[PDB]
Length: 367
Ligand SMILES: [Zn+2]
Ligand SMILES: [Zn+2]
Image (spheres, rainbow, N blue to C red):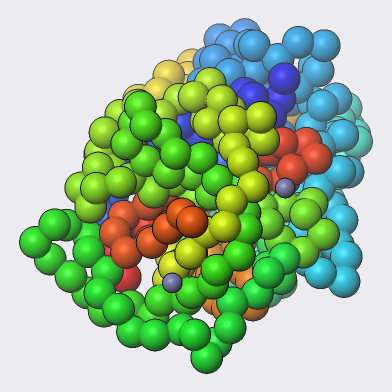
């Protein structure tokens, strides 16, 4: 399945980010998947095999990555009085550049992509600003400057973008009166102050005696989405939890079968994470290499070989407060009885419960 392939890709990414991200980590795997899916639709041969492999689409059973992405996107684009979820894809092309009508039709149909043309050739700065400004408009202005200066030139011919936006009330809101200053330990011998929200209510909970950690599910109102938190038992237990975590174990540890309704004294910080990623080298390292060099085959975009990707950028935001949470991200592809006290490092993610998809994943290491 496509959701399962997205989680695996998510954990592959995380193992890479652990090398260059010392503190907080936060991203939208689905955003990245959706962008690179749009690329896949116009890739051929080994350019296409590499992408498929890196994203785990070679494991998606009934071309059908795309069919499935269309379902997923329709399922995600739902807002309610209690939350909003939105995911939008767009192609910005050089106004003079021609794409195959079949590539354009395919991205419109499977990825709901809107197509705009811009003047990269003579106004690349202004084109860059238009794109950044569209992203802002899709993310309640939480993702600003997705594409910084110099990642677009007069020779840029395409920018494929995914934006994802979520804002949700908690099913059980925290009382702001109960929020208090506390110590947050990023390391055993070190602390930063933090605003700690506190609540005592029941939640799905499990003790993972094996990895010496706990899991909690914190639902949004309506329960169409939840934030899941994984908290090591020890201040410094995160690395081992990180070493042990795989797609299968996550699915195992976070299924309702393996959790139980439990009264939990939940202490969760008010927090915000903003992180930017240049993914070109990360993606090459994981196996996507033709796409970025002279062996690129993106002839399914234009009728013949010649397009190469110059860049892939990702930016993500999340803020957690007493009322709920707001999370956004965007991806640009450029072509030419129990306690649960979160006062030390933890992993968290926002899950779409119906599809069982992970929309956003992160590590909170330090305010
Ligand atoms: Zn329940
Ligand atoms: Zn308490």
